[PDB]
Image 1 (cartoon, rainbow, N blue to C red):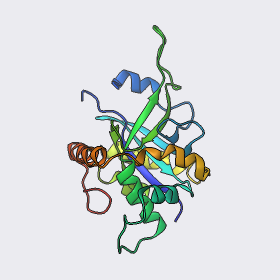
Image 2: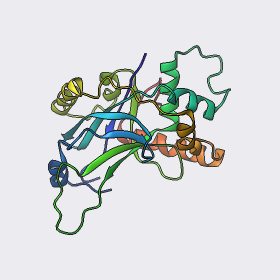
Image 3: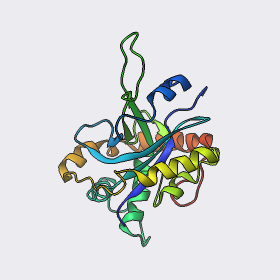
Length: 220
């Protein structure tokens, strides 16, 4: 019950182009970063509990805790999705997030020339509804440890630092309420073609494999 968690690399060094020197300057952020859907203001469903500078890139762990979100997604995706499966609300939310918001996008501000990066650079993390462009791959799960576990390449140092900062975030236990109607406008994109979804799901599958993240419950 309650919160679910989300993790991923915001960017990969050497492979939006954030260098090491930029990331060092931007962390830790000025204020905790909200999580919204597709950069929609007034559409916060969560918060980033921590961000660390792993050797491969900045890596984040987030909480999502919006009680209306699961029913708006379920309604969007429609009555036949889960078949005969017996599932809790939390589980249903996890399947829906993993198949309809399978990627994210770090919002960083465009800097004027000669303006050095500082800890206000990163504003928030959008979870991206599946569509004509997919962002960076994320993993969802029921606990922080489970959300980060599929990322085997994350250094031991960054993993413990991440889980320990997160365990102390003031945002850990928040709840984000949102209107049925606001969420519905934000999530309307989940109602575009089979063309667009089958093609995007293949892209997402390939990108997850490239990122080393595999599973049988929520991932494939």
